[PDB]
Structure formats: C-alpha cells, structure tokens
Length: 182
Image (cartoon, rainbow, N blue to C red; front, side):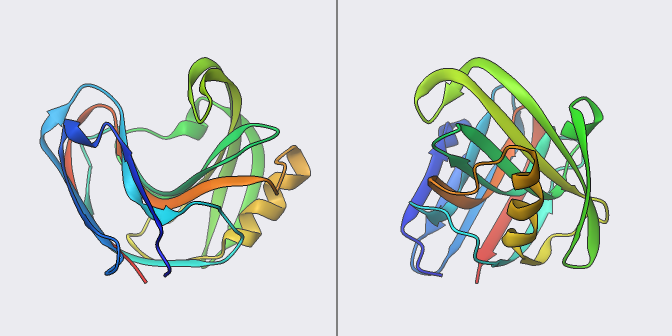
C-alpha cells in the first residue's frame, strides 16, 4: 500500500505492534484503557484513493472504532469513516448531515465541533466529520472519494490533507484488534 507513516497516539496505553512493509499492525488493550489512544498505519499525505483492509476486531464492550482516520490542514478537520465500533456511536450525539451509500451500505454522516482539544497543531478548535457504517464489518474496501465528496457539500475542505491511516481507537474499556492494509 506504500505505507509510509505510523500513527501512534498513546499507543503505550496498550500493546501496539506493526510492520510497515507488510501493512499489518495489531493492538491489544485487554486490560482496558481509561484514556484515548489512536494507532495505525497509513500515509503522510491523505488522498481520495480507496483503502482495502482486513481485520480481526473485538471491541464490543469498548468505546472504540475501526476506522479510516485523518486530518485536513485548513479548514482544520479530523475525520472518520467508521467501519465497525464498540459501545459508542458518535452520530448519536452529533449534528446529522444525512446519509451516504458506499461499498455495500449506508453510513450515517454527522459533524461536530471540538474546542481547545488535542489536534495536529497541538490544542485547538476543529471540526470533526463522521460516516458511521450502518452494517458494520471488519473487512472490505472503503471508497474514500464517496465520503469526501459528500462531506465536501458541508464544509469539508476536500484538499490540503495531512496524514491518513487505517486506525483502531479506544478510550474506555478493553478490546483487541489485528489489521492488514492491502
């Protein structure tokens, strides 16, 4: 996949292993976590190219996501295309933007504003964009373009991309995850 970036945000909170060249990574937090971590493999500059992945993901009792994750520099935005998740749906609370259909399923799409929080610039106010898969899965292709195009109708800059990775995130509870990016 031309993986050239390792995402490790508090990976030390659980057990994070990875092989850039194989496009694989695992992450165990079986003892539970009480703080947020985001780990994964990807690219230093994001693009609208499709991402194919395969995963073993077990996070039923955990506030966790198995998602395509990345940032946009300006307007600053953090984004997720959540394929599978734990006990928490971000669109349950956020402002609804509609629905989008892609790769065999509809995704609820929502947005939210984070004030003075950890960001690719340290601490700041940024916008989040979420596409949550209606029929969750742990393997398949994500045609990122379909999501970027829909979000772009609502403010998503759709250019000036920072990093983008296939990620696993959790900030409560315990779980397990093994992922391969093809």
